Length: 439
Image (cartoon, rainbow, N blue to C red; front, side, top):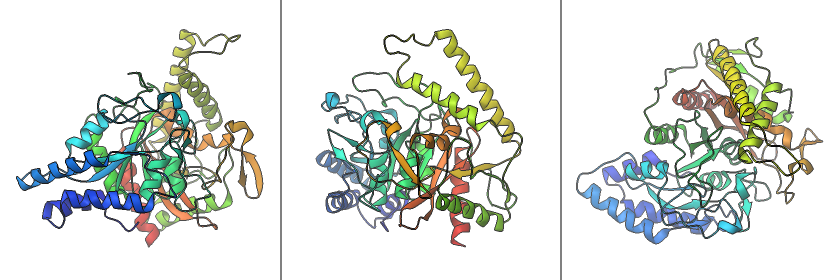
């Protein structure tokens, strides 16, 4: 995976080092040579993408340039591409062919990107694994016996094995940060509502899930993410105000009242913070303005179940009332205001993405029957939603970036949470953390 970044590829084409057809063909080759044991790129559109790369070469020949002109990428299978299936892993929807490009795909195509195909997902996007009966299971390129993460697991696998330089996923339950963390790549959970969800539709519907969930880019480096964000946000977002770790105010959370963290994950996160502190950052371990993380886990869980159920209840059970739902949105807004106050005293929160590194494949559907080994002991699998709850419930942007490996060689990720609409700041703090950690 020493491969060219997306910005590098475009510049390669813009100076003439290579053609857009050459770059497209190299990515097709990397997928065929590398994807057999990984099974990340489960929907392929190679003939159409080649014709498209030829088109982009005719553009550059005519003087045209665009920030992604000729760069091959793939996208999560749940995001519509005109002419390709969108199934979300349901057997019933394996042959649902999308009729329109999603808005993200439209934007990236308009910047000149070329789509080779789509990457794998769990059934209903409801797992931190990617396995389903239409395409099968994606395996972590760092260790084929372990999960690639989910639900943007294919995207993260494909990035980690260097197939394509850019991807785009979705996150309602960690589904961008968790795969990026398990496979050792960068994933940006964006500020709520900052990127349009048009085309991230439940198959056969033109409805999206209008609370909690976001879409955001995935790459091997922070510069590709920043560019991919600028090209897809519905409007232009504030530039990074940060430009140095000197004086940066960091809130370091290695403990969570609703979930444990393996000693190696804690150590990795703490070492990210000490590197920054050594570059002049001021790191705190507690603060009075920090919201009740336990209450927040429960409020996020209650809302998440209602959203995925679309407000329906089993029979013998009364649905939540519209009025009570409005009350829940008020509770949400109150918790968000809590974080606004915390971010008056802090530029970023550093914490785990998850309490473990990638876990071994699990055939058990029900999460209440899974465990995770944490410092030698079995713990409840579902508890780990705690770590990703803050930024989904309260809308904040949140980066997952690689910071180490555990003793078995599995990637370990750091989560960087910044204030709503400061997504470029989360990317920039990550780049600077990578510098300090090289130091």
